[PDB]
């Protein structure tokens, strides 16, 4: 149901917050350029792909940064100390393998070690001294990501690093490929630094000044053992999630019901989403200048913020389909 | 290595957040006006000093507000109750002397008393009743700062109140004096209300709309007894600190390595800085309008947010030197 | 320094306790058969490789079983519940990828999830129901291992799943290849079920009735950050570890000093090992029948019992060299 | 479905660990002798019943010892202090009636009293002094069992003392009665001291030196209120339990699947069993000499180690049937 090869390209490219230029940026440009009229990279690094249109100016954002680690200190015996880039949980770093980025397109392996908190965490790269670690290419500021790869789980699911929000990057790339003569002036934006404060969404939206804003991200799917039914949020395979509200935004009620009606009419599976504590690029877009009516579609995902995030292709397909239909009909809104 | 008299003038002028006009504002205007083309004070009180230039528009910000206290209630027996202005720790108020500002350029002494939290803290000014305290010039809203003075510690260090961020104010005043025919349109800004939310940096940056932004502040130097080596952050005397990231900003990687290369070329001592939880004016500047590439240089400082902050003149000199070199070469960036 | 390809073959073959026949058994037989006179597999599954000799009967054992998990229940929504095979720590299962063995040479992926203990742990294989999980080939008793691969760390180190005790299996395979006309009747034994009670070592030793016994295993290398010097046990790269005693055995003092003297004479790096709480096959071998004088050589290893165990090739080489020298000179003991 | 009278005879005969000769031993000999060729009692007290056969030597063991108490001290006022024989839980001794064995076939009643642990537990036998208690026949070393009797619970269940492992003793007696011209040399063994360390199974297996070993015991049935589905282990009435592994043994996988296939072919209800922490005679048998391939069939039982253990006759019948079929077909294995 999804273009596996394309998905693999987007989830495995390195791109931690602030350092998206190290890999994901180029993948996005290369995969979207032939489907739009112009592609630009702004000051903070956001990739803005414009598909000239016949109607309302619409911004569709998916963040391309992923969570990761940054080297803060190199111990005398060569071990590395780190600080999180984004919301990283120490429990997900123990006895894990990492890709320590020493240069663009070049990494060395590392092992995370020693319920822990940051002061007990360290990375082992096989060095015997600080000098050897430095000779290997490591320094203060070196970025690190988990060593994770995309794999299939059963008939319709997948496991991978950075499904948040790379599955959304995949989604807008697919939407850009499907969109044909839409009555709208579309700006597809792969935003930077969402994981540290919705920073890229804020600056790109200011420059674009859209009439409507849409964000695509992942939402919690806690449909797992031991979770009370009312706390599952969303279920894998039950459809794209239309956001009603999260801690950063209350989606425009008119857009929310409009999307729901579109899903019903085109027979696209969907589910309604409410989060008590979360954040999305929509949270920045809607507060741009004099205000922007916004909506958000999410891909349900289990185990968010780890090297083993899980999604269902049926929800991914529903998201691509609903966003495409929204763009084709937004001129009537 | 530093102009002691000038430093004394800037650290001892009163200027708590929101009330910078009571003292520090005028010191800044008087000390910088002869080195720039025009000096303005905007709506929130930011001092903007423009040195007309031949190149990129660059904003350099140092906040002039300091942390302090505000009187919230006067007890029946004349004692004062207070609320913090900025991040003040109760442990730093016990058995301390204070300057209770009753008017511009006029203060009376006070003694802080009674591990405490705010509900146990009170200030004694020698009054016997609420009426006597009011007759002495105190009222709800009266601002208070520690009674601290600048003094030398050994060969290269100093102790003082408000080194954060007055040492940065000193730094930009020194940079303005050294800058000669720079290929850049420079805006030196002494910002207000940084300690309560980077408020002045936000509004001044919006009005200036710079091409590049640089903030100068202090960074944690925890190179003291009992601190694990990997948690010291920076070391006094080891150089100006080039920020890679803190909780409010991920400095543009191109600017970060550019500054590092400049330091190497001109033989200026420097160290790389990463903070897990902090905030700087750069955090506001870079998110201005469509975005602004930014960098930050910091002066390592021990015991931040107290009446006994400590810095090393060698780091201060390195900061002045690196910022000056950056401004002289930014046109090539 | 090590035969990387051979090591990769031994660490990546599946073989949890009791189920060594699923993979590792055949790798061992295939890689050792051409270097010995006869190869047999006994009742519990131990592989016994006999190199007919001219002297004392010597048994050299390395266990081929690795720790893992076994499916105990399949939940209504397709999730799997597990029980440990060997000493598995729940902290090493969270947000990890696994290979769920549905048949010999056939696996499907799984994700471990939800400080935890066994009642909170579960594996997600992408199934939507118990029936779908069963159709995928899973049942009560299905065995599972981490999805780990051998990789290099720096100049001399490696990271891998099951270095305990696969690095010892590699070692005896290398010793069997090097041993030439030794004055001893040698029995190389790849034992089963060491992780659950030194079970295979017990039964194979009874049948062999050796004059001398030697076990090769891994020992704790806690030469990592935060560990007091006296608690590091061994250091990576400092040599093969000659065991003095652990909780299961006090090595024969004559053999211990004999090995130390051999290491000194042949210039083989070594270190002395004492463990307060551990267990090795020697613990079973020495208590066989009327008793067997035994010794043990260990490969220092960090992060034991995880998917990211780390060893140093210099220690592996020293172990192969010392065991080879011991076999060539044991006739003089 | 079961021979009620025979079951009553086996569960009510006294026979705590080490003292099986006081009652159960003779019941076993009397009930099995006419179905075998020879019956012997070895040194530790194991009853070995040999049914001469035409094939593989097979040992089938069921332990005849039950948990109980032993008098450790007689207080000045006649109360008795005790120590457990086997894994006894103090909570099962409070406000309970006991049979204090003063001689073979002679007992007096006692009452257990005063969440408790051993130092608070005592038995009241109606004595007024230590001298009177001694005159009643009690001394240090006197053994005690609960005063429990076999009774029916509903249509298919029963409640009784010592179903562990007397229900297995009943099972082998029934198998011995059904076995006819089996192609195997069968040794039925009622083992001693299983509850204190699988001691009798170890010594009898050494003497028999079987080709195959099978143990019959009870397994946990926690299919009761408040137990999570994945922690129930087995369910009453769902069939004989084929053990995959417990803490003392990993059953030979070939035998496990062979038994499962036999159950399927003969339409005998069965369920697969995995225990995280338990122990069975198989744990000793399989490690005998050079090793013995073993399997174990268990009768699901609720409330194990109490005076109110509960089993289902349908599971007992399935166990007798599967063990009989295994013996008749083992020659093909
Ligand atoms: As998010
Ligand atoms: As600050
Ligand atoms: As071990
Ligand atoms: As038992
Ligand atoms: Zn996201
Ligand atoms: Zn996220
Ligand atoms: Zn500051
Ligand atoms: Zn501050
Ligand atoms: Zn081992
Ligand atoms: Zn182990
Ligand atoms: Zn039992
Ligand atoms: Zn028992």
Image (cartoon, coloured by chain):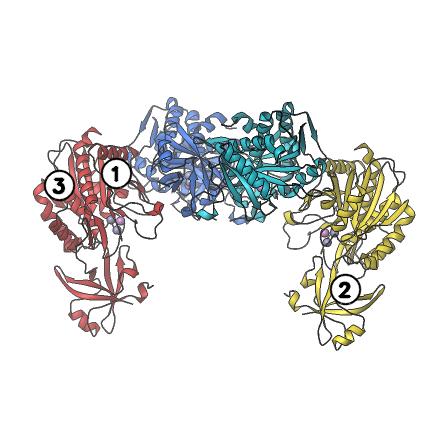
Chain colours: A cyan, B yellow, C blue, D red
* Helix, strand or loop status at disc 3: helix
* Distance (Cα) linking label 3 and label 2: 97 Å
Label total for image: 3
Disc 1 is placed on an element classified as: strand
Residue at the extreme left = D34
Badge 3: residue crowd in 10 Å (few <14, some 14–19, many ≥20): many
* Subunit that carries the residue with mark 3: D
* Image mark for residue B165: none
Task: Give the crowd class for mark 2: few <14, some 14-19, many >=20 residues within 10 Å.
Answer: many
Q: Nearer the viewer, mark 1 or mark 2?
A: 2
Q: Quadrant of residue B224?
A: bottom right
Question: x and y percent of residue C22 in the render?
Answer: 36, 30
What is the spatial separation of the Cα atoms under label 1 and label 3, in whole angstroms?
18 Å
Q: Residue at x 75, y 67 (%)?
A: B140
Q: Which mark is residue D295?
A: 1
- Front one among C223 and C108: C108
Image quadrant in which the C terminus of chain C is located: top left
Find out whether the residues at labels 1 and 3 contact each other: C-beta distance under 8 Å: no
Badge 1 density bin: few <14, some 14–19, many ≥20, Cα 10 Å: many
* Quadrant of the displayed image that contains ligand 10: top left
The residue where tag 3 is placed is D176
Image side of residue A275 versus residue D89, left or right: right
Q: Picture quarter containing residue A75?
A: top right
Tag 2 subunit: B
What's the residue at 79%, 33% (across, down)? B333
Q: Which residue is mark 2?
A: B144
């Amino acid at each position: 149901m999804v273009d596996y090869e394309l998905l693999k390209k987007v989830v495995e490219a390195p791109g931690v917050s602030g350092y998206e230029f190290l890999g994901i940026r180029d993948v996005v440009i290369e995969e979207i350029k032939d489907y739009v009229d112009e592609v630009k990279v702004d000051k903070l690094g956001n990739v803005i792909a414009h598909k000239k249109g016949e109607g309302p100016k619409v911004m569709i954002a998916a963040h391309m940064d992923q969570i990761g680690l940054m080297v803060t200190h190199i111990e005398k015996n060569g071990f590395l100390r780190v600080a999180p880039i984004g919301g990283v949980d120490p429990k997900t770093l123990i006895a894990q393998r990492f890709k320590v980025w020493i240069d663009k397109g070049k990494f060395i392996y590392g092992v995370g070690a020693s319920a822990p908190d940051w002061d007990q965490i360290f990375i082992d790269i096989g060095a015997e001294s600080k000098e050897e670690a430095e000779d290997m290419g490591v320094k203060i500021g070196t970025v690190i990501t988990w060593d994770g790869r995309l794999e299939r789980l059963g008939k319709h699911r997948f496991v991978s690093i950075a499904f948040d929000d790379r599955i959304a990057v995949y989604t807008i790339l697919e939407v850009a490929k499907q969109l044909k003569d839409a009555k709208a002036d579309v700006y597809f934006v792969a935003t930077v630094q969402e994981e540290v404060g919705l920073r890229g969404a804020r600056t790109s939206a200011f420059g674009i000044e859209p009439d409507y804003g849409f964000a695509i991200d992942v939402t919690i799917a806690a449909d797992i053992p031991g979770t009370p039914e009312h706390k599952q949020v969303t279920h894998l395979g039950k459809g794209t999630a239309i956001k009603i509200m999260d801690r950063s935004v209350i989606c425009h009620p008119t857009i929310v019901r409009w999307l729901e009606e579109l899903a019903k009419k085109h027979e696209i599976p969907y589910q309604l989403e409410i989060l008590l504590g979360g954040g999305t690029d929509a949270g920045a877009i809607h507060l741009t200048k004099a205000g922007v009516p916004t909506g958000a579609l999410s891909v349900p995902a289990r185990y968010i913020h780890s090297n083993t995030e899980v999604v269902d292709e049926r929800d991914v397909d529903a998201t691509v389909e609903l966003m495409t239909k929204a763009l084709e009909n937004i001129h009537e809104l």
